[PDB]
Length: 226
Length: 230
Ligand SMILES: CCCCCCCCCCCCOC(=O)c1ccc2[nH]cnc2c1
Image (cartoon, rainbow over all chains, first blue to last red):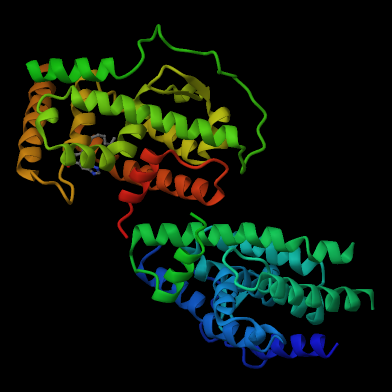
């Protein structure tokens, strides 16, 4: 309740006001393979969500009560899933319009060189997500359920499960006020999309036009199970 | 050249004769669920990779001079070229007009049976097989070209001058033969398509390691890790 209110406040504070939106670089008709500028932009757009998602998670009630190690581990493990889910929800797949958490608005063709195919899969997911007409409260719970989840190497797993359970109840409680099971149905498809992001970074690291910035690199390495 | 004879012997010994082709697992049509794979598809993918390295190892030991390079230079050349060699040899021996992959053991598998294990990569390899086939490279030239892919400059060679020496020798053996029967610049034009296909193979292994239905065999894994510049 106060939980839901807290989760909603943290969500809306973590993104641009419809008025803080910037179309000054938006182009509805532009025209090759990726160059260094496309790869820089890809890393820059990813990097732009790092501090924002960190500050969002600190405002999730209970999140600061977890061990610093479990905090860092949860953030690293969900970063990509969180970037995708939040971009999918904020974006306008009907116009092929990507809206980033800084307020930057770009057409798919303007990011497509950097992201590759993954951008199309993300837009497919955005359309699927948009179709379920998820309200902000539900999404504020969903996004937190993506963060506060079991990962390998948690010190206090029981406490993470506890807090997940609490957020899950706050969500069910709100939805009652199969629809739940279709919301929760989008967490595994989000993990599959996470995989494509790891594939793309792998590929970009191979190609090495521009190296990933240290923090993305660490997320990449620390999130490989092998 | 006695070298060319040696190079041809090693090439022809390193694959099936048109008689020892094995259709015991071939199915002209299977109905796969695409974009996914089971443990059986992934084990076979690794087994086909594994089997090609063992055959390519034995082929390279038959290249005159190759056995007298340092053990370290031998391993480094084999690792560095393995994927290019697997692709080039598979492209050359395969029948893309019948959608037929032919492996160095003699095993024949339809495009659709390889789709689950290999993904897209198998289709790009068939595109390359067609491109390669259309250049009408004879066995002697290909026996030299495959060796030139192996015996080449790489970072971390202990005796690079000796590798260049042996490269030079195999290069002359090739020129001498192309003049004898009488496309080279045209062959070199398809070297980026091959480099891309090497990238696609690293992408596929990456993905399969992520997925981890079955672990990669140690030797393929070491080639994967040692072959990533980072
Ligand atoms: C159909 C495209 C290529 C088929 C084989 C012809 C090329 C022979 C080997 C490459 C050129 C001579 O050797 C090299 O300098 C060399 C060797 C291995 C390489 N791997 C990637 N680039 C390479 C270049």
